[PDB]
Amino acid sequence: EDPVVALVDTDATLRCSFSPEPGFSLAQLNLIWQLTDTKQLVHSFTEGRDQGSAYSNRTALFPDLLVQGNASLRLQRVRVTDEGSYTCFVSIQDFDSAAVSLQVAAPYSKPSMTLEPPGNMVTITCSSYQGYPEAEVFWKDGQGVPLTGNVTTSQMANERGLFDVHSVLRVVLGANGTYSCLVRNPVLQQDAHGSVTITG
Amino acid sequence: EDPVVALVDTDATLRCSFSPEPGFSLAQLNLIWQLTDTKQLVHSFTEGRDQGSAYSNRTALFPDLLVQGNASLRLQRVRVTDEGSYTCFVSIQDFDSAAVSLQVAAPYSKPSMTLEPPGNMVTITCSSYQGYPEAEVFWKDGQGVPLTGNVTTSQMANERGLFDVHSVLRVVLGANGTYSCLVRNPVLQQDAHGSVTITG
Ligand SMILES: *[C@@H]1O[C@H](CO)[C@@H](O[C@@H]2O[C@H](CO)[C@@H](O[C@@H]3O[C@H](CO[C@H]4O[C@H](CO)[C@@H](O)[C@H](O)[C@@H]4O)[C@@H](O)[C@H](O)[C@@H]3O)[C@H](O)[C@H]2NC(C)=O)[C@H](O)[C@H]1NC(C)=O
Ligand SMILES: *[C@@H]1O[C@H](CO)[C@@H](O[C@@H]2O[C@H](CO)[C@@H](O[C@@H]3O[C@H](CO[C@H]4O[C@H](CO)[C@@H](O)[C@H](O)[C@@H]4O)[C@@H](O)[C@H](O)[C@@H]3O)[C@H](O)[C@H]2NC(C)=O)[C@H](O)[C@H]1NC(C)=O
Ligand SMILES: *[C@@H]1O[C@H](CO)[C@@H](O)[C@H](O)[C@H]1NC(C)=O
Ligand SMILES: *[C@@H]1O[C@H](CO)[C@@H](O)[C@H](O)[C@H]1NC(C)=O
């Protein structure tokens, strides 16, 4: 740049320039015109808006032209007082984002078993403590095979969000049956079991 | 990214990343970690400083590692409540500057001439009005040749900064002399003159 010569009482243009990326949008652009030496503010374009002229009320941008990278300032009704160096600061912000999901877990304790002590309906109870998230519960006999029966299973969360699972199987008996509870944590893939065996 | 699995009561790390330019410095970087859905603030690094953890007091950056582009966040003493998606916003600011100097000008009016009316010391007076900046003043005879003599020249600025120049030449007379004043504006390179001619 050479200096800009302006007749007193006329309007003048102070050049400034940038090269915008194809992405570009004015919400990115942050633009300050300042008196070089003092660093007093003259005109600003920030946060997708054209703020005013700061003190003068005699300055303007070419708001239709910014997006194309013209940050030149227009100074009106020039006067001796305006003489000096002006500095144009142009900051473009490129914002990127990434997301990350946190999955929380806790293990369930070894279950504790309970019943009402051979063609009779009896109830077995599986209780396992303080795991997260909700567990998958499986009842099965001693050779891995699902037990038939009515099972009620509830899972109750404490103050800290952790679950205690309480699962109740009502069965009719067979003289030699083992009965098992597997409490699974899907997320950790940890398995907890207990089992009663009934002969007599 | 896959999701991050954290045992309750342990510490976990949420990854985030950037690729910095060789220029790069932390005063450029603006960094927000937010709960994706709510958009509540978790942790920020702005204006060359690491602001705190926002609400939790359980979060940290790796401040020694930012400059290399690691914006990962450390979450401490994890709990069910923390479960969710987190979003990391990374804005880098590249600031450029240019300076432009405004040189103001105004033209001087045609000078007006005055004297005390042939081997006598007389005084001629050049007055020119409202120019800017200070002018160069030249006294000369009628064939372009500098006049010898004592010249006093003063330049006085009005309310608006503009100069009136008043230049006084004291000469001894020669029976046939033309006397001239050239008032020059260096900046505009406009010349203003007046002249008296003296026969009798
Ligand atoms: C940013 O956009 C600006 C807004 O359009 C551009 O400004 C324009 O620039 C063009 C090309 O250089 C100028 O065209 C020239 O204008 C002069 C007229 O004389 C000057 O004096 C009057 C005062 O009476 C004042 O209005 C201006 O300062 C004038 O420049 C002609 O002699 C030339 O032949 C030619 O037509 C436009 O005048 C100018 N417009 C304004 C309002 O300044 C600028 O070029 C762009 N900058 C960048 C970096 O891209
Ligand atoms: C940003 O910088 C981070 C700070 O150093 C980097 O984090 C480090 O990443 C390395 C490489 O992947 C990890 O090394 C692995 O760590 C695990 C240890 O188990 C995890 O569990 C404990 C909880 O008890 C917890 O401290 C962490 O979440 C652990 O990751 C090992 O099994 C691996 O073999 C290997 O050693 C560092 O542990 C990790 N440090 C921390 C504090 O997280 C990160 O890689 C950088 N990110 C980017 C984008 O560059
Ligand atoms: C600047 O302009 C506003 C109108 O937008 C006006 O209210 C204010 O008084 C002006 N200030 C000066 C110093 O001219
Ligand atoms: C966060 O930490 C500051 C100490 O830096 C402490 O004064 C403030 O009470 C903390 N807030 C919470 C909610 O723990």
Image (tube, coloured by chain):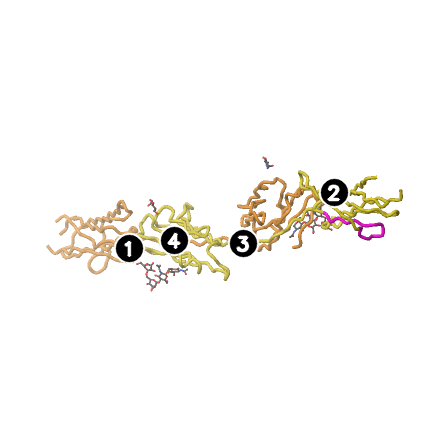
Chain colours: A yellow, B orange
Find out if the beta carbon at label 3 lies less than 8 Å from the nearest ligand 2 atom. no
Query: In the image, what residue type sits under mark 1?
Result: Asn
Q: Relative to B69, is A60 on the left or the right?
A: left
Q: Is residue B1 magenta?
A: no
Of residues B148 and A166, the one nearer the viewer is A166
Q: Chain of mark 3?
A: A
Q: Residue at x 36, y 46 (%)?
A: A55
Return the x and y of residue A127 as percentages of the image width and height: 76, 42
Q: Residue at x 56, y 44 (%)?
A: B49
Q: Which residue is mark 2?
A: A166
Q: CA distance from mark 2 to mark 3?
A: 49 Å
Q: Which residue is mark 1?
A: B185
Return the x and y of residue A46 as percentages of the image width and height: 45, 50
Q: Which residue is mark 3?
A: A95
Q: Are marks 3 and 4 in contact (CB under 8 Å)?
A: no
Q: Are marks 4 and 2 on the same chain?
A: no
Q: Chain of mark 4?
A: B
Kindly identify which numbered label has been placed on residue B101.
Answer: 4
Name, please, the residue furthest toward the front.
A119
Q: Are marks 1 and 2 in contact (CB under 8 Å)?
A: no
Look at discs 4 and 2 and give the one toward the viewer: 2
What stretch of residues is rendered in magenta?
A135-147
Q: SS class of the residue under badge 1?
A: strand
Q: CA distance from mark 1 to mark 4?
A: 19 Å
Query: In the image, what residue type sits under mark 4?
Result: Ser
Q: Relative to A3, is A170 on the left or the right?
A: right
Q: Are marks 1 and 4 on the same chain?
A: yes
Query: In the image, what residue type sits under mark 3?
Result: Phe
Q: SS class of the residue under badge 2?
A: strand
Give the tally of numbered discs. Answer: 4
